[PDB]
Image (cartoon, coloured by chain):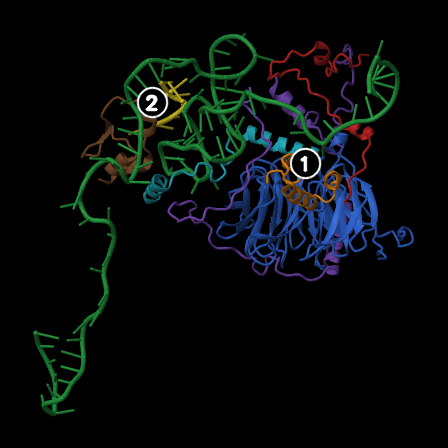
Chain colours: A purple, B orange, C red, D brown, E cyan, F blue, G green, H yellow
Amino acid sequence: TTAHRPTFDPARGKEALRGPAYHQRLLPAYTTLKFRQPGQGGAADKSTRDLRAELEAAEAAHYAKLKGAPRRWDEDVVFKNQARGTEDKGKRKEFVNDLLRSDFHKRFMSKYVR
Amino acid sequence: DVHPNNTQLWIRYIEAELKNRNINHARNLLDRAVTRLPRVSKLWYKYVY
Amino acid sequence: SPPRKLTAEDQEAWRIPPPVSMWKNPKGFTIPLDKRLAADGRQLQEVQ
Amino acid sequence: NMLNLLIHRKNLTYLHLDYNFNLKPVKTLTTKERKKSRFGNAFHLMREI
Amino acid sequence: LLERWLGNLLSRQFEGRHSKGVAKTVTKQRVESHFDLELRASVMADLM
Amino acid sequence: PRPDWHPPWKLMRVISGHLGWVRALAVEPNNQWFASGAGDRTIKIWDLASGQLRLTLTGHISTVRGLAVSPRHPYMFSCGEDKMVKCWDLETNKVIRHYHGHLSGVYTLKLHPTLDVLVTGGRDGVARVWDMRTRSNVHVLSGHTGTVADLVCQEADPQVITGSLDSTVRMWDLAAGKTMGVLTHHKKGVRALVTHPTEFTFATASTGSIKQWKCPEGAFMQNFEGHNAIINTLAVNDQNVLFSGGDNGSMSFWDWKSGYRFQSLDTTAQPGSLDAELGIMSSTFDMSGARLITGEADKTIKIWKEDTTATPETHPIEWKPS
RNA sequence: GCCCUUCGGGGCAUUUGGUCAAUUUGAAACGAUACAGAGAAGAUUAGCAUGGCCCCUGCACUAAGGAUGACACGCUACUCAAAGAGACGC
RNA sequence: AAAAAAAAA
């Protein structure tokens, strides 16, 4: 059947109706605009090269901060030392762009599907 | 109005008014067509033909 | 700007296959079993 | 009289609003009559006030 | 509240229902259908 | 025209952290932090120097397709594919206003630079002009026959220029809410617009063609040619740098006056991304212009910096006059 | 009608309002009647949308419902040819 | 301390 259909021509916006007002639609709320006070920044433009210098100084400061520069009881046991290198996970937390193979999905699906 | 830059619709409307000997109507249509769509070779060919 | 000079190679390069669904058939069509099994890559997968 | 005029303007005369403000159908309603008659919270809250 | 409600009731009574004036929000019963609407529009724009 | 020498741009920092494509990007006037809205329905506030995540804000139920931090007010505006345009009070980190009325998903959002007006563009094919204070839709700029994919506000006529996916670009007189001109030079959907900050010119980008125009006449000034991809974005510096980012992942840095492409790149995708997932979805220079923040379909914010090592001789202008 | 006057005169107050009450011929409607038989390629079926010269209930013109509210299911030349070979062709 | 949810000559 073709009762159930896609959209190939989505609905188009209309201008407002130029009619007499009787209907109530939007109750007033937050009718006062806040402005950036002195100290809240924004209302001060200095130049371009000063901004570039400040940006590069902040980047150099962050890189400086990151760098830091100013009978034995276990002898009949069949297998010994099976857990070397297992605790070494956590060298650097790494992002994989696959939500089916990310570590979050594996943790989630091992927690829940028991 | 719904399809302004459609060449098939333009040719259909021109030919529909040419089959009924409305020559002045069809020449107005062809001027409007090659004004609307100046880089469509089919409309220009149809007007010269 | 003046229209792009296409070739028949380009027209063939932009042919969209007719879609044969493995699930859906809203017109109740009878499709040949060759074409139904055309996009099933499972038979053409590798085993080793 | 206001609620009575509203009821009669909507052509719902098969609902009697009595003088103690009870709205009752005067007859057995069809499905379309029931669907058209269901009033709102504004009408009913005003009627109980 | 009640004068607002009665004014809107009388607005429907005397100037009619505006059936599709303002856009309905994407409530929870419309989430997946809306995602489909937007997804299909986006894929079509990339192909066109 | 002899082009100027511009240093080439290289990848500085890669910031993972969204779970959907980064479609929006907006820098504070004070250049301290920037705002990435993404397909994981969220707006993240990141510090610009360190790159660290400061905050995550969730108010949208669809992908965030637009952001703006107001230079006069302590507000941040957003729009999304959920038909919603919101005003966030950054003194509380909470949504305080709604701008309702778009019939379907909203693709772009700009603020008028001088006066307190918000213009948004949408897949209902229309650009709605809103008042910030009263949330009232003062104008419904209509006449496009397709999705309004990008939009710029300007301090003088034409105050609103909208580019749509039906390939036309309309310039709108804001006082009357009616168009003063249509530019039909583009063959396919005009996804990007940008305005030069010091010259009274602008640029529109469709697939393969980036055309540069003059205000208010809409006079065809020149044509950036060579980027044969779907152009999603456009970013001009103060030092005449046009950035064409392209949905296949292609990056082109042009000189604004001459049209000379002084750099061409392909961006790199994260570990795990498909080759289909290589593509630039958003871009903006910061307020200084020293950095270019791009957001890509491998769910990644990338920062691009100028190479200080390169000289005018190590990368000479290979421009051949005709 | 009052008030002033030098008895000649003058003053205060100033234009309301929707064919009339008049039920056929200026426009209200269901019921009721004969009926009817609730969508998704066998059967039974939960829905959520889409577009608007289709609406109804509702404060909701930023809910929800009305069979998933219904409508949808029809029609179908027209940007239009090219080579090759045949004909008690003409 | 209502709706779903009881059908178009």
Percent across and percent down for residue C28 are: 60, 13
Query: Residue at the spot x=38%, y=39% of the render?
Result: E16
Does residue C25 appear left or right of residue B42 in this picture? left
Does residue F75 appear left or right of residue D22 in this picture? right
Q: Are marks 2 and 1 on the same chain?
A: no
Chain letter for mark 2, please. D
Label 2: state its secondary structure.
helix
User: What crowding class fits label 2: few (fewer than 14 Cα within 10 Å), some (14-19), or many (20 or more)?
Assistant: few
Residue F267 sits in which quadrant? Answer: top right
Q: The residue under label 1 is which amino acid type?
A: Ile
User: Above or below — where is F219 with respect to F61?
Assistant: below
Q: Which mark is residue B11?
A: 1
Residue A52 sits in which quadrant? Answer: bottom right
Q: Nearer the viewer, residue G74 or D31?
A: G74
Residue F251 sits in which quadrant? Answer: top right
Quadrant containing the N terminus of chain F in the rendered view = bottom right
Label 1: state its secondary structure.
helix
Q: Is residue F117 visible?
A: yes
Q: The residue under label 2 is which amino acid type?
A: Thr
Q: Nearer the viewer, residue F250 or F168?
A: F168
Q: Nearer the viewer, mark 2 or mark 1?
A: 1
User: What crowding class fits label 1: few (fewer than 14 Cα within 10 Å), some (14-19), or many (20 or more)?
Assistant: some
Separation of disc 2 and disc 1 at Cα? 55 Å
Percent across and percent down for residue F77 are: 58, 47
Query: Which residue is identified by label 2?
Result: D31
Percent across and percent down for residue F29 are: 65, 54
User: Above or below — where is C47 with respect to A91?
Assistant: above
